[PDB]
Amino acid sequence: GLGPLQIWQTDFTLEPRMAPRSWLAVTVDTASSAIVVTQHGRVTSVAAQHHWATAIAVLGRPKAIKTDNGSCFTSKSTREWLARWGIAHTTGIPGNSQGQAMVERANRLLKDKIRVLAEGDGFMKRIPTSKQGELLAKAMYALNHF
Amino acid sequence: GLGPLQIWQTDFTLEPRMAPRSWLAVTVDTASSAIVVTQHGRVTSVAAQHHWATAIAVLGRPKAIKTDNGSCFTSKSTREWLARWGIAHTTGIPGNSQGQAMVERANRLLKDKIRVLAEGDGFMKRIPTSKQGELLAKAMYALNHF
Ligand SMILES: [Mn+2]
Ligand SMILES: [Mn+2]
């Protein structure tokens, strides 16, 4: 009734430890603080849609999503994909200074967690491609569950 | 305090509409009835571990998981992977008749949902490989969120 509005913040951040699919798409559900992250080979409009398809399966459909003005978020293709799901999109104030510190903070916690767990498994540089998926899933678990 | 025990049921089911990665690994969290499904090319011990890595990221670590005696669930490799996470594993009673109707039911709801959504998009036989991921994610959303 009076609980938080279901607003997500989403952003992409680069992580060479996860190459070749080094772009991580990160969504923070601002009502719960849960984090959803997926890995992608290139930052395109279709990679953002594939990330949100997975975040929806996991967190439900939000009422709105806030992003920056990155072109994979403002293309015609991504605007139509969000209209097909009935989700409102805002890039907030222009020179907003950033109405998305929560996802910015999530991005740093996430890359720190990835580094600490990868180094615990003995991977000091790039994580071998066949170990990436389970280590990303472990970083996600660690940041969402207590 | 007196709520449901965190027990999952997991099973693999075959779905040719999703070929080549036609094996679907399905986990039902018996306390919440939430469903987690991932797609795999072969039914192996590593495909079950990769599915549970993702289910853990999404639902948290359970106290125990019930499966059938399928060899990808009873191998040495899968038993050690569950011991590393500290999760108890039971295949229930031997000739239990099936202590896993919930996941059995989830399997049929899931393949029905996949068929109805794929046919709504015009795919009457196999779903094209590049449309699979978003349609699986849509079937998962539809069965978990109201
Ligand atoms: Mn950005
Ligand atoms: Mn089975």
Image: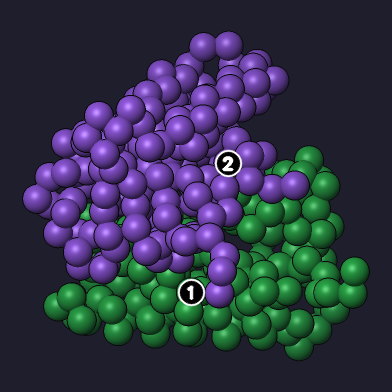
Chain colours: A purple, B green
In front of the other: B5 or A68: A68
Secondary element at tag 2: helix
Query: Crowdedness of circle 2 by 10 Å Cα count: few (<14), some, many (20+)?
Result: many
The amino acid pointed to by label 1 is: His
Q: Amino acid at mark 2?
A: Met
Residue B71 or residue B62, whichever sits in front: B62
Quarter of the figure with the N terminus of chain A: bottom right
Q: Secondary structure at mark 1?
A: loop
Taking the image as shown, residue A121 lies to the left or right of residue B62, namely: left
Residue at 43%, 70% (x, y): give it: B141
Question: Could you say which disc has been placed on residue A5 in the image?
Answer: none
| Position above or below: A2 against A11 | below
| Residue A113 image position (x, y, % from top left) | 61, 27
Q: Is residue B26 left or right of residue A57?
A: right
The residue that label 1 is drawn on is B145
The chain ID associated with circle 2 is A
Q: Which residue is mark 2?
A: A140
In the figure, is residue A60 to the left or right of B45? left
Q: Position of residue B114 (x, y in %)?
A: 35, 77
Res. B11 in view = no
Assess whether mark 1 and mark 2 are in contact (beta carbons under 8 angstroms): no
Q: Is residue A11 above or below residue B104?
A: above
**Disc 2 from disc 1: Cα separation:** 21 Å
Q: Is residue A3 above or below residue A144?
A: below
Residue sitting at 16 percent across and 36 percent down?
A71
Coordinates of residue B117 in the picture (x, y in percent): 28, 78
For disc 2, does the CB lie below 8 Å from ligand 1? Answer: no
Q: Is residue A20 above or below residue B53?
A: above
Mark 1 closeness class: few <14, some 14–19, many ≥20 residues within 10 Å: few
Quadrant in the picture for residue A72? top left
Q: Foreground residue, A59 or B58?
A: A59
Residue A34 visible in rendering? yes
